[PDB]
Amino acid sequence: GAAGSTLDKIAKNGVIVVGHRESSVPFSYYDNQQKVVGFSQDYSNAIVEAVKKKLNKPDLQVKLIPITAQNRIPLLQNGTFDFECGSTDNNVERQKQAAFSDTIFVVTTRLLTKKGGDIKDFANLKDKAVVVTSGTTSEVLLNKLNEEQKMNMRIISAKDHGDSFRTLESGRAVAFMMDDVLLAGERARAKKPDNWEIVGKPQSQEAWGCMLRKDDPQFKKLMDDTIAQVRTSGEAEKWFDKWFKNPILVSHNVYITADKQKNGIKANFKIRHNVEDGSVQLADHYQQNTPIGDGPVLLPDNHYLSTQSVLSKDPNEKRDHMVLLEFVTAAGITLMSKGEELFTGVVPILVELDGDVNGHKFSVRGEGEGDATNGKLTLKFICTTGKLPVPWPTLVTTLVQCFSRYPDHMKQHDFFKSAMPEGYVQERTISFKDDGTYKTRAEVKFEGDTLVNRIELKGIDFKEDGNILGHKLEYNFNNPLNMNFELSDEMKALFK
Amino acid sequence: GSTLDKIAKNGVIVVGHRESSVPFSYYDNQQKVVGFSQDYSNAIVEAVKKKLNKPDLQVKLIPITAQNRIPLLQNGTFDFECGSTDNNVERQKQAAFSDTIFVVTTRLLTKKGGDIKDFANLKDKAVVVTSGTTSEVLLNKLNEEQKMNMRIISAKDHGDSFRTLESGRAVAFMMDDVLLAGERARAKKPDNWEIVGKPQSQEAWGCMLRKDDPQFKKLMDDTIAQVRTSGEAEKWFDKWFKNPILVSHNVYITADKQKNGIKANFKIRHNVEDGSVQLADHYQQNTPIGDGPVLLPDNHYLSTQSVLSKDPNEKRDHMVLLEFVTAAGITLGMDELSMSKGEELFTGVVPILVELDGDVNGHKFSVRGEGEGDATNGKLTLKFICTTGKLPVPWPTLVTTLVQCFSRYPDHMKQHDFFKSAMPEGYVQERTISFKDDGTYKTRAEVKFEGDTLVNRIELKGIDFKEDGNILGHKLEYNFNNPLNMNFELSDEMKALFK
Ligand SMILES: N[C@@H](CC(=O)O)C(=O)O
Ligand SMILES: N[C@@H](CC(=O)O)C(=O)O
Ligand SMILES: [Mg+2]
Ligand SMILES: [Mg+2]
Ligand SMILES: [Mg+2]
């Protein structure tokens, strides 16, 4: 058979081509910024890093390409990609065409259906439209059940799992059959996740592995070693808790460019606020910052800030309020001044905002602390004038980028700290799609030991029953997904 | 101390600028401060950098108005300003002036075909003027001396003054004639407006600086003299007054290392025939067609300008395009005052073929373009034809869809040129273009060499467009980059100045 390895081909070419799935949630799927993410993609990344160390090629490139259940094996055999980790069952029939790593997940094949409907088990599918994803194990099982039991099902074959779920969600099928965890994943992305139930006696139990070409023991050994190390280091259980037991967030990217004319910077970015009906409210941000002082600043090369925030409520606070936890890291440039020295400890923060939106006047006061070493903010905001006339999430970006974590190799690009203590003016236009606009002007500076953000906000042209003045936005940030899925006994055994 | 002493101490020169003195010192639609006088301001800054041996001197532009320019100069809030300030004896008591950079007369702007033919026609009428200007003094003086009973509306800056006139809330706007021509150029309908009236005065503009600083005055006067005799002053006049003024677009690029590619985002503003603007938000992702190594960039941007024209011998629906693109956003380092194989494919002139098939709200169409690209100069020249008859969308909405491998990457940035590095195998370019209050284009293109020709083959799908919106309604001007075209003669006094 083969005398060489895909590892030798990778080393020659300088790139590893990795297949990935498009809608295997939360394992290998596109997030709303088209990043390929998930539990299996974490294994894929670990394997890629293991290939880089094994080949001593620290600058190896990666090229992720999309595959489907239908085309994964033909594209593997003709060399279109080198391996994939996503949601592929290891079985005997497939071992005739491909090789598999050791198992990374174990599932059972079940049904997703509307809560409170007639579908309790597979027997309820008689004479009904049932959706299943083309090219999958469940498609084979569902057709076989339909034929062997003469159930008169109308089996709809959809191109990928999100399409299958949206067939169910729109009423064109009474149930979706698939791996139970993938049903839970599509449910998490639904308009109303809590309307959907997993039901039915399992038709099978399956084990997922990474797929690679046959006759490559060196590459499979590197994968199996990597999987073994992920387990015994505790990372496998930590990745499970990450994807299945905590909110899954999508980072925002604040794109920064120098504005040398003004000795400052500009930025642009988009926020997508979740709407209660399952849609999204786009908020387009334009930003300009100029230093208050007339001394030197750091004028950055282009880069971006990667941001995630968590909103919560203080159970002992009766005023209208928001508790905020925020994490920000600078990126976009590949690998002590006075201003930067001001941020080496924990710095108290004060925020004051005076707002007028469509004539509705309000004020907000916030206090907390920031830890730029860790890119971390913790703040509590109160509406001091009574009820806030807009949703708290629409004010998050307005309510101190000097607390971003700049990596050591990027510290010469940190405009925000360099303007301290005298500070900077931050101005934004925030354009809400199909609705009004906020215009903001803030001064961010030190007053004594405290970092103060004092803002004026003016909002115009809002729709009184739109998503903002109508209070139709969910109290969250970064478009969370929250899985509802039990750690099974089989998975517990896998982790030993 | 002196102004240079302050600049040297701080490492920053603080430059006052006007906000609406068109086309001398004004904000363009990307908030950049531009104009004929700002070209002088930049020349002065560069002379200060050279004099102080501080190539990394920083610049801080701060806005000033006709009302606050002198007090902010006096208390040191800024160091100098080049804009539109008259030099006169009264102001010399408060400030020093450079040698003259422009000469104007004070006149009126009014609606073409109206009753305002000269200053006498203003009797009993509303007249607008900018607060704190020479014209405001002259207009009030004329009012009282000739008992004209004008209602003088005093607006905060020249754009506000003009929009008072444009919106019918005054019958005329008095100002420096060239500033009237500048505000006209930005109007909803520039050709509706006429400059009339016997000049009330002739004025000379200079750059303002603090009094009793002869060395800083000499640096500015020396720079202004060099601009004249080097011919730059006449070239700047031609640039600002006899050629279209464009705004550049910035294409903001970030790496997408997962896909061995890049993403980009940027905004295009299309001029609408009624004077409004149609926003087109661009999201972009590129991936290499080949599986071999590429250049993965740090964040940077492409600075783009385009000129659309018509071929007078072409009877088909068509667009002639000239485009210039330069990469920017990574500073040339103090210590430095081919990176891919594909880069070598662009050292000379490369022929280009573009093929687009479109479907917008069910209206199908095809476009074919041919021309050539010169990446050494960041320059493209193409002619496009609609091969299916009439184009069902405006040509400007297709410009961004219809080869960023022809961008000029400065030498210090060549390691960030993903586009050329993916050749000859090429790349896939996908976009979502969202037209504000209207529909969306989704595009997928392959850009690659086919033999010696760089080929861009595109599929475009448009949905949710309004049939009477700006796109399907064909309400967009045939231009790009939001041009302004001055209508202003070179006077004999300006010719004298250029000697
Ligand atoms: N695990 C199933 C479904 C999938 O791949 O998404 C299969 O291997 O066919
Ligand atoms: N040139 C006039 C108007 C202006 O400054 O814009 C003045 O000096 O007041
Ligand atoms: Mg939801
Ligand atoms: Mg009199
Ligand atoms: Mg126009």
Image (tube, coloured by chain):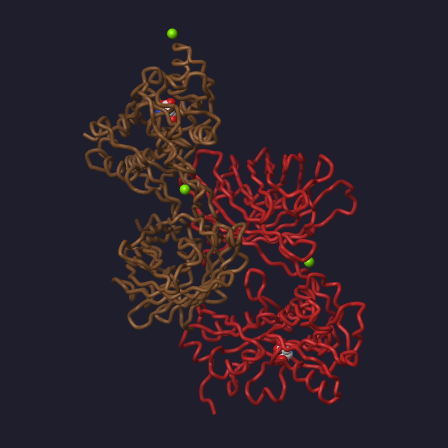
Chain colours: A red, B brown
Question: Measured from the top left, where is residue B497 in percent x and y?
Answer: 22, 28
Q: Nearer the viewer, residue B127 or B44?
A: B127
Task: Look at the image and tell me in which quarter the C terminus of chain A lies.
Answer: bottom right
Q: Is residue A134 above or below residue B72?
A: below
Question: Measured from the top left, where is residue B428 in percent x and y?
Answer: 43, 67
Question: Measured from the top left, where is residue A485 in percent x and y?
Answer: 73, 69
Q: Would residue A490 be found to the left or right of residue A272 on screen?
A: right
Q: Nearer the viewer, residue A25 or A223?
A: A25
Rendering quadrant holding ligand 1 = bottom right
Question: Residue shown at 70%/74% (left/top)?
Answer: A176
Dividing the picture into quadrants, the one containing residue A237 is bottom right
Question: Measured from the top left, where is residue B468 in percent x and y?
Answer: 51, 51
Q: How many marks?
A: 0
Visible residue check, residue A426: yes
Dividing the picture into quadrants, the one containing residue A487 is bottom right
Residue extending furthest bottom?
A1
Q: Would residue A67 be found to the left or right of residue B373 on screen?
A: right
Q: Would residue B115 be found to the left or right of residue A228 on screen?
A: left
